[PDB]
């Protein structure tokens, strides 16, 4: 039932507080997520948001050639990236993701599930009950396989290929983490209040 | 581009 | 319904399988031909430990390349892409190969099918955290109990990664991967694994592997920061040097 999922300084600070809000509310609208212990929910979010965010705009940038569309509609051309020293990482997103997403015509349904899998990452350290989380993930790509079997029966390998973008998505996630800092430098437990409130 | 080539 | 592999696919299956088999060290008698690395070696970047891994890593690397050459499709690629594919999936496949050789009774991995090392040993050997990533994987693959074929297919798919940087015949490589994946998916249907969600679960491993090779790449940078350049074998360098 990925239908409930599909239905789901003063300048730069305006966003993020909105993106993060939209991400949290997106996760809350995800099956069984709001049922997990408070701590287990925040740990997941904080362990995935990187890839989740990147999975979002990567699919949104399918309608753009050699560019990325972000929250503020601020289209980003690869000319700025290479000029900012992030050309390499930028290109990966276009070829490994944006490209692959376009060439397969990945729909919002598939994107949503893929992002749902990501969230339910049972490997995340510290969470109280992993068995329960990996359960949820199973149930998640359980639906995904059936969707691909009915929605696109003329292509059996679709389901499979859908997952094989997560790897790319992962390693790219990592580069972004290494690139960006600041937030992390704010010591541990810098963000938990909000996550506790949105909860 | 080196030892790889000769191994090919 | 579960579509079993076709005749044109079984041909590719026996091809890849044979390709893996002839290139996996110690064949099927690895358990008896393995030697436990001295518990003293690598205590809590151990020069000694490292020197032993690197002293047996070059055959592994080559054996990987041999697996590639025993694949017609791969032989159809330009030398440019041919090199790139290897450089990328190299650490991944070796990792797979090592991880599928995990022994719960001993909690050790078998490098080159002859060298048993523990989590700690392989960690202090230069890999560091990667070691965990790998052992953990091996632990996970334990319940899968993959056979040569299913392992060969993974290696096959790992090789044909159409997202490696600098590739030319991208749509060409991607087509190959799609071929393997098709047969891969059908083969397990044939195997009729009784476990729930086997195919997906397995595919996630591809994520895990791609992340290992990556952390390994960052490890290599730190390795040449601590360890000397002379302690590195030529082939090894060429493989992970830009
Ligand atoms: N056992 C594999 C071959 C294999 C050989 C070795 I040495 C391994 O450890 C590494 C690898 C890279 C490094 O930089 C360091 I330091 C240690 C692994 I993991 C695998 C096979 O059977 O193909």
Image: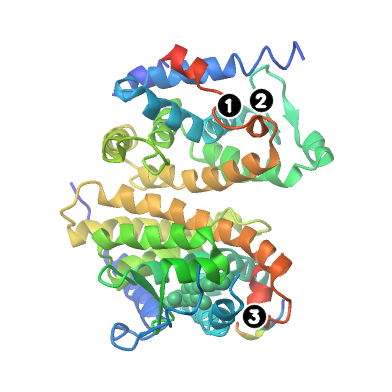
Q: Residue at x 49, y 81 (%)?
A: C63
Q: Chain of mark 3?
A: C
Label at residue C235: 3
Q: Position of residue A74 (x, y in %)?
A: 72, 20
Residue topped by disc 1: A60
Q: Nearer the viewer, residue C229 or C10?
A: C229
| Quadrant position of the N terminus of chain A in the picture | top left
Q: Earlier in the sequence, mark 2 or mark 1?
A: 1
State the residue at coordinates (38%, 67%).
C99
Q: Nearer the viewer, residue A103 or C225?
A: C225
Q: Are marks 2 and 3 on the same chain?
A: no
Few, some or many C-alpha atoms within 10 Å of disc 1 (few <14, some 14-19, many ≥20)? some
Residue A107 lies, in percent from the top left, at 45, 29
Where, by quadrant of the figure, is residue A151 drawn? top left
Q: Position of residue A85 (x, y in %)?
A: 80, 43
Q: Identify the residue position indicated by label 2 in the image.
A: A69
The chain containing the residue under callout 2 comes to A
10 Å neighbourhood of mark 2: few (<14), some, or many (≥20)?
some
- The scheme the figure's colours follow is rainbow
Q: Alpha carbon of mark 2 to alpha carbon of mark 1: how far?
A: 6 Å
Is residue C104 shown to the viewer in this render?
yes
Q: Residues within 10 Å of mark 3 (few under 14, many from 20)?
A: some
State the CA–CA distance, disc 3 to disc 1. 42 Å
Front residue (pair A191, C19): A191
Residue for point 68% across, 75% down: C237
């Amino acid at each position: 039932p990925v239908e409930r999922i599909l239905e789901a300084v003063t300048n730069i600070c305006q966003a993020a507080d909105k993106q993060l809000f939209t991400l949290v509310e997106w996760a809350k609208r995800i099956p069984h997520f709001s049922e997990l212990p408070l701590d287990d929910q925040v740990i997941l979010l904080r362990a995935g948001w990187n890839e989740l965010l990147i999975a979002s705009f990567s699919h949104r940038s399918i309608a753009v050639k050699d560019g990325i569309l972000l929250a503020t509609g601020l289209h980003v051309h690869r000319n700025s990236a290479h000029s900012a020293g992030v050309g390499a990482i930028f290109d990966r997103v276009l070829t490994e993701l944006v490209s692959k997403m376009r060439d397969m015509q990945m729909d919002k349904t598939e994107l949503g599930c893929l992002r749902a899998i990501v969230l339910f990452n049972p490997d995340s350290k510290g969470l109280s009950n992993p068995a329960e989380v990996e359960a949820l993930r199973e149930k998640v790509y359980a639906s995904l396989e059936a969707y691909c079997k009915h929605k696109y029966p003329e292509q059996p390998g679709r389901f499979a290929k859908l997952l094989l973008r997560l790897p790319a998505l992962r390693s790219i996630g990592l580069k972004c983490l290494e690139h960006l800092f600041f937030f992390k430098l704010i010591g541990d437990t810098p963000i938990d209040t909000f996550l506790m409130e949105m909860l | 581009h080196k030892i790889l080539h000769r191994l090919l | 319904h579960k579509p079993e592999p076709t005749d044109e696919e079984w041909e590719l299956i026996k091809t890849v399988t044979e390709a893996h088999v002839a290139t996996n060290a110690q064949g099927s008698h690895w358990k008896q031909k393995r030697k436990f690395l001295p518990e003293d070696i690598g205590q809590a970047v151990d020069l000694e430990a490292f020197s032993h891994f690197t002293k047996i890593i070059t055959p592994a690397i080559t054996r990987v390349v041999d697996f590639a050459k025993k694949l017609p499709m791969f032989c159809e690629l330009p030398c440019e892409d041919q090199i790139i594919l290897l450089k990328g999936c190299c650490m991944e496949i070796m990792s797979l190969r090592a991880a599928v050789r995990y022994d719960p009774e001993s909690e050790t991995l078998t490098l080159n099918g002859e060298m048993a090392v523990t989590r700690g040993q392989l960690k202090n050997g230069g890999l560091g955290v990667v070691s965990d990533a790998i052992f953990d994987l091996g632990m996970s693959l334990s319940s899968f109990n993959l056979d040569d074929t299913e392992v060969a297919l993974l290696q096959a798919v790992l090789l044909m990664s159409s997202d490696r940087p600098g590739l030319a015949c991208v749509e060409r490589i991607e087509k190959y991967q799609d071929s393997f994946l098709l047969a891969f998916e059908h083969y397990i249907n044939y195997r009729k694994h009784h476990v729930t969600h086997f195919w997906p679960k397995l595919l996630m491993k591809v994520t895990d592997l791609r992340m290992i090779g990556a952390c390994h790449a960052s490890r290599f940078l730190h390795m040449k920061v601590e360890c000397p350049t002379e302690l590195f074998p030529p082939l090894f360098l060429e493989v992970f040097e830009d």
